[PDB]
Every structure is written in structure tokens, then in C-alpha cells.
Image 1: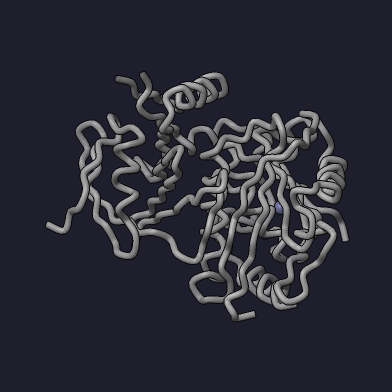
Image 2 (image 1 turned 30 degrees about the vertical axis):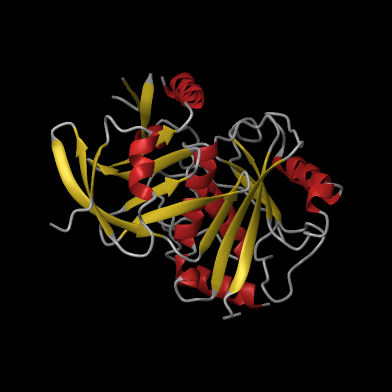
Length: 334
Ligand SMILES: [Zn+2]
């Protein structure tokens, strides 16, 4: 009928998922998914207004149309699908290279291993991660997030420089999963034509200690940027340092240089706009949250809001606060 693709989520590997995603460009495509005895249809389309550069190659984002509540990522090295199953947010991860896939599976086995992590094999085909479960097992829930220091229509291109900490362990698909959440949180600025967003992912030779204090870590990050010849003259963009782990002995997931410091018309220079962020699947919206702060958003008391003041599993990657919208709109115009 209006079906264009079939996909068995249990048996699929990279070529299956990429085979589907690479054919989706301008129009909505309808896909029949199967997981065990459950078969259902969903529709997705490519996301416009965003560009991702990873190893000097494009990465593409996809999303469900309406109530579909599905996202996907297509890279030349991996692909992912994120959707809701039985009320849980589920990540399906496929890497093109079998060795890399094995390394990725080992990561999830060592860090989470009722089934939070499922590995489908023939030789691993894909990895299925229950994000909701993974979040539910995290500590510090309810504790106040402490992630910033105390005190236009063109469409303007906003480019985020995402810098991978050396030996930081950030996984390729985690970075673009974090980016997807940023993209969702900023849709209201993108669909309206206020901005287009570019995410530039780069390796660095900048290392950090595991338990380091966030303020020192950020400053150390910025000092590295200022003498890094690879980014010479690109000092007027937001820079975020990415690691798989955390700061301050597990208590800090991200930290922004300031609130409301990104301005499209008169951008700050000398790498003054920066943040650090985990990329861990256990903290899927942390990058979007930090960038929220950089754009002017403040903590709020709505637990569904991206900018919720406390760590909770109810958080969605959406700015639901009208006041934060006001703050962000006023900030970027400066
Ligand atoms: Zn915060």
C-alpha cells in the first residue's frame, strides 16, 4: 500500500538499516517494523535545517511525523533507530565494521551487564539498549543540577564545534544521539527559519582526568582551544568538550561557561563560549541541556522540561518553558 520498506529489528545489521535510511530524502517514507511477534508501521523523513560533519563526512538525522515518536541516524560507519517500546525509550545500534560493532557491544556489556542490553547475533548484528531502564538505574536522581557559574531571521547559521576529549571514550553514535536531542530542543528556532544548525565533530589531543572538577576542566579546555592551530581563527563559535564519563566523581554531567552567551549578530570571541558534556547513553540530553544554558535557558520546575533543575527520568529534550523561549530569543538576537 503506502509501505516502502520492511525492517526486522531483531535481525537487522548496518546494511539493512542503512539500506532503508539512505533512500529517504524529501518525502515521508513508511516502514513496516518487526520485533518478534510484533509488527507495526511507522513513517519517518529526513530532518532539514541541520548539518553534521563527522570524520569529514555527512551524518543524517531522521524523525517520525506525528505521534510516531521515532528518530534515526545514518552515518557511513553506523546507524541507529530510537523509538518507544512498551513505554520505554529503546536504542537500536548497528555499526558497519564488525570489529567496531564488537567493541561497542563490549562497552555496553561492561557498563550495564530485565534486559537493559540485548545483543542480537547471527557475529553481532545489532545492539538494543533500553535507555529508560539505563536512566532508572542512575544515582543522584533528585539532586540539584549545578552546571553553570554564578553570575536574526536570516536564517543565521549556528555552528557547534564538538570536540572529542582524547581517550575520553565518547562513542560515535552517542555523540550524534546527543546531537539529535539538541536538534529536537531547537526545532522551534529551526522550523521558523530563525537559525540553521551545523554540528562539527572533531578529534583533539586534549586529555582530562576522570574525577576532575568541572570549573578547572572547562578552563583547561578553553586554554587548549586558544593554542590549537586546528581551530585558529574559529574563536567565535560555541565549543563543547565531549567524554563518555563525568566530572567531580560522578556528580557533574555537564558544565557551561555561562548562561545566555551565544549571540548571532555579535558573537563572543576568544573561545569564551564553551561547555563540557558527557555523551553517555545514561545521560541522553545533557548536551542539549548545556547548550540550552549557553543560549539563555534557565532551570525550571517542570520535570518534563529539558531544563529541569533536578536529575529525573521524566525529562524530555524539549524547551517547554515560555520564559526560556523568551530568554533564548532575546539572547541570540544580540
Ligand atoms: Zn543546568
